[PDB]
Image: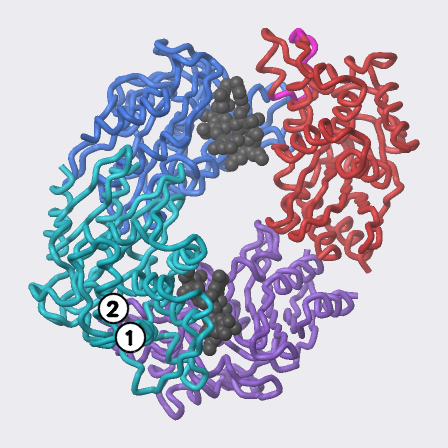
Chain colours: A red, B purple, C cyan, D blue
Amino acid sequence: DLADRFAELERRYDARLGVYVPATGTTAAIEYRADERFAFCSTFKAPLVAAVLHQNPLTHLDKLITYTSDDIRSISPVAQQHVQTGMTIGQLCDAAIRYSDGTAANLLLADLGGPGGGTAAFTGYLRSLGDTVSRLDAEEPELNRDPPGDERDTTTPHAIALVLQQLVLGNALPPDKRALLTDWMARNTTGAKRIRAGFPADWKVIDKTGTGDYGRANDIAVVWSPTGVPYVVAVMSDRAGGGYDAEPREALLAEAATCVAGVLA
Amino acid sequence: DLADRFAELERRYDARLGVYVPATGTTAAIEYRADERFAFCSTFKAPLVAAVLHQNPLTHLDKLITYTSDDIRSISPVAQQHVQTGMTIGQLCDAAIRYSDGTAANLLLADLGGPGGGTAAFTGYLRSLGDTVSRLDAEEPELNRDPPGDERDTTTPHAIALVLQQLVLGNALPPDKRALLTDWMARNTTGAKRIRAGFPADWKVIDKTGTGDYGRANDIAVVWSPTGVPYVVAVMSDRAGGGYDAEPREALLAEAATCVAGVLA
Amino acid sequence: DLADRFAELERRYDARLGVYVPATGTTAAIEYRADERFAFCSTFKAPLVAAVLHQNPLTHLDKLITYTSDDIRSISPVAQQHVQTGMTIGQLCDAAIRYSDGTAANLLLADLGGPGGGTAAFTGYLRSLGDTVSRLDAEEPELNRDPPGDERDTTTPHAIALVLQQLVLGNALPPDKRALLTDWMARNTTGAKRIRAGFPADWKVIDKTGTGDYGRANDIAVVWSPTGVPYVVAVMSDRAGGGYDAEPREALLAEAATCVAGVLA
Amino acid sequence: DLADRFAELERRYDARLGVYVPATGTTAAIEYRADERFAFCSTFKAPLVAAVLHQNPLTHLDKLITYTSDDIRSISPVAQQHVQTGMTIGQLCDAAIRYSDGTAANLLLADLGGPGGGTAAFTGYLRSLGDTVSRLDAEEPELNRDPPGDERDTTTPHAIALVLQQLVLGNALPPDKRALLTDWMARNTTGAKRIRAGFPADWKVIDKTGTGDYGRANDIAVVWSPTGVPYVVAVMSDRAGGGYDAEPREALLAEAATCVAGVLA
Ligand SMILES: CO/N=C(\C(=O)N[C@@H]1C(=O)N2C(C(=O)O)=C(CSc3nc(=O)c(=O)[nH]n3C)CS[C@H]12)c1csc(N)n1
Ligand SMILES: CO/N=C(\C(=O)N[C@@H]1C(=O)N2C(C(=O)O)=C(CSc3nc(=O)c(=O)[nH]n3C)CS[C@H]12)c1csc(N)n1
Ligand SMILES: CO/N=C(\C(=O)N[C@@H]1C(=O)N2C(C(=O)O)=C(CSc3nc(=O)c(=O)[nH]n3C)CS[C@H]12)c1csc(N)n1
Ligand SMILES: CO/N=C(\C(=O)N[C@@H]1C(=O)N2C(C(=O)O)=C(CSc3nc(=O)c(=O)[nH]n3C)CS[C@H]12)c1csc(N)n1
């Protein structure tokens, strides 16, 4: 009867909607296509920064990474302003989470090192979290482009929600690093019209968006009730039936979120 | 399931909760104790103003109403400061709705004329709108003091939603007067922590609160979805079993609001 | 060049304006007719409360004072709701400051005891604060009605500002009682259009209004800058040239207040 | 004496303050560094939109503008979410004014056409309004990064105040387009802590902010007194001597505005 509304949202927006809200002490899990695969798009950038924070002392944030204009591919509002100066790892994190900067994501992946420009190590980091389903295989911007049915660069609402839960509410990171990740997510600039727009203002919402082709629009959020109770909300969506150029529907995610807000109220 | 969620709100907040949202083309009616009686409190001030607008040309709003300190018998944030100046009917309407001014309501009731200082005339106005259930019996401040179980000064969420629906979305008032009422409710200063607090920010909420003893807390709203689709939302609550001094719990109204929002999204 | 703006305001509103802002460490005193006499009106109710708190061991706030309808004189939104209940001193304090309740002020005056229904003791309380200038001679509502030029029931902006300064920023009261007075002033419901309306929202404003005949409109405030710097602002006004029935002008007080805010920024 | 207070602010905030308020019938102009050059930053986005409106029939607002990830080279809260969807000229105007979107500004500059990617046409539009002083030389984001003393991408408080005056209060724009601009400025989301924070809440403030390196913080506003009298407030500031990374002091602009309000009250 919650599922009835999500599928009505799917019909409204001609979209495939994936939602996961992990169970807590007081609420049952919310699952709609919780285990179907959806493309990460930029949502991997949040666990990416967690991986970077994990592998390395806080001090590593100050390392200056220089890069060239040839490295700038995909939306990079911050990295485009810093080719000449370079960027520290730390700000690369900042840009990757708060602005969904793709160049910053690629540099952080390279900083993870290893085959596929870091994707195997980032996949590995998710595994160290118990997420065996998700995988990152390409860099920005290729990871937004895989056709439907392709398992590359996909997660599921279930897996990615649980990952975020460990990163923000659990002990994946020592409190020092958990605060930095949580702060960047909290000051994200890309999610205003998604999960943030679907919850009442007095719910705190930290989130990481993802947007890609085939109408891919994701949002991963930690939301706090007015009473301060946290819930992890994974909302993922695509419109593959509309082809590569199918437009993402931000309103779809805000609606799905309001529905989740209604069950969490 | 929605009824189940309301029942938990009721249990959580030691309160009796009444919710009504009239059906639309796209949504079924939402009813929880839709036909149980709850005390008006200052929620009557909105149809009160409608009555004055209905039986008077607009220019009647400019009429100067003078009154004495002896008329200041209830909380009157605006009327208390204008004993020496007088106040126009227009100003009284504004004060009754936006500040829940009790003297302004009594003076608007007086402007209605008839037995009981306007209370029979205002009830009659509810009758001409098809509300056979509601009744206003006392003035400010007595109408907030009636004991639980007494039908005096009571309405139901069903009835008041239907009244508010005709006033804001229907043709109870010509567009002239409808705009003035809609504006006053829209700039209401008392409802931020009630239905407004439960709906996402991109929803428009115009509302009239009511608060009284026995933990009475009401909010009647017309809300517009981001798509611009209107809904009438009546939420009434009391904690009468907690006696006269029971504190109203606004968060219950915000929670009930969020649940409704989740079903309407 | 500030006197030029106040006298501008006086000319605009056909009014006598009295302004006093005590000097602080960094700012000079602001004085406009700071030492001319203005009628207390209800502004005495705030130091009245400080008097009651000063001479009683706090438990006295719970003492129940009963009164009769013949005792209800002048604007009394709270007292006229508690006749069969009576009202505790605490409630009377709260009513006198936050609602300017005149009946509550008279009962607190009586509770100070002595000739003239407490007015001599209250004057005496002011003397203990170093204000040798002010005097209270009548109860509500007579104290608002003295003709211009009559020294009875008058203070000066200078005098009341320093009095309020000691009550809120100094040590007239022990910290317990100072908290009760300040909180009452902070939640005052009567000053929204006076000093409060002249200062930017991010300046905190606690205040006590006074209004009377001859266009008497006062507001005494303690204001806190966005930096948290306190200032005492006494703004008093009458329009005696317009006779007993002269209307008070709140906008004069907000404008004068804005002028002050410009100097204190 | 106002100048002395502006100098204190300058000392207080280690900042250079530029203030202009054009004369009206009742008030003399307020000038402090009125003819000194300050960097535009995003305040140009307001006349930029007017330039687009001036050159185009309203019908042009619905024209769909498409762009690529390479166009996202500066902070673009709205445009970065619409690379796959594209954006309407109207949306771009809205985004440029209300969210200070850097990409929306560049597309609107491009919409003006001509040398420097629209920069010459925009400067010319300022020239056609009688602004002989101001110049736009770079697009976003370079136009925020000119070193102190460099005249590129600078205006004066005098010039921009007069430009803003003609746009909102004069006849630079026909009434239909003038309302769209005024509406966009009125719903600005970035000016809460500047001129708005320094004027009393009952003053109406529409504004366009600007922020850049060297501690640059501007706010240009049209403000209406409670009586509805309009005033243009140009406040510009930088902390250039503090180097590229100086950060802006919004409270300086709010404090400066409070000073202006006190003289205009
Ligand atoms: C929740 O996000 N809301 C935003 C939004 O998109 N804001 C962004 C955000 O967080 N921003 C930040 C920064 O990253 O710190 C900034 C600073 S960006 C910057 N800092 C420097 O130190 C520097 O040298 N150069 N630059 C360019 C301002 S707003 C933009 C917003 C824009 S308008 C509005 N009403 N809200
Ligand atoms: C005899 O009357 N008794 C009253 C009474 O006058 N109630 C009126 C009523 O319905 N009113 C409304 C409103 O419109 O909701 C209100 C509630 S608004 C409000 N009040 C606050 O103190 C506050 O901090 N925030 N907000 C938002 C004002 S009282 C009036 C009363 C008030 S509390 C209580 N237990 N009884
Ligand atoms: C700060 O002033 N602003 C006001 C205003 O006048 N609010 C008042 C204020 O502080 N109020 C209070 C109370 O006494 O706590 C209340 C409580 S009234 C009340 N409470 C009881 O417990 C009871 O037994 N009886 N009654 C009557 C509600 S608003 C009024 C206002 C009016 S509309 C709006 N948005 N604000
Ligand atoms: C290369 O450009 N450099 C920029 C820049 O993008 N400037 C633009 C400009 O003028 N903008 C404006 C605005 O409209 O004022 C703003 C101010 S918005 C804002 N962000 C916050 O985080 C916040 O807490 N409050 N507010 C109000 C965003 S940057 C853009 C910059 C911003 S801070 C800094 N040191 N440089």
Q: Which residue bears the numbered disc 1? A: C113
Q: Main secondary structure of the magenta part?
A: loop
Which quadrant of the figure has residue B64? bottom left
B221 or D91, which is in the foreground? B221
Write the residue at 85% across / 14% down. Answer: A116
Residue D56 lies, in percent from the top left, at 41, 31
Q: Which residue is mark 2?
A: C121
Q: Is residue A41 above or below residue A252?
A: above
Q: Can the viewer see residue D177 in this picture? A: no
Tell me, yes or no, if residue C250 can be seen here.
Answer: yes
Image height of A193 relative to C140, above or below: above
| Pointers 1 and 2 in contact (C-beta within 8 Å) | yes
Q: Is residue A144 magenta?
A: no
Ranked by sequence position, the earlier of labels 1 and 2 is: 1
Lateral position of residue B173 relative to residue A203, left or right: left
Say if C83 sits above or below B21 in the image: below
At a point 17% along the width and 57% down the height, the residue shown is C132
Residue lying furthest bottom in this view?
B115
Indicate if the residue with disc 2 has its beta carbon within 8 Å of ligand 3. no
Please report the bounds of the magenta region as a residue range. Answer: A66-77
Quadrant holding the N terminus of chain B: bottom right
Q: Quadrant of residue B156?
A: bottom right
Apparent side of residue D139 relative to residue D4 in the rendered image (left or right) = right
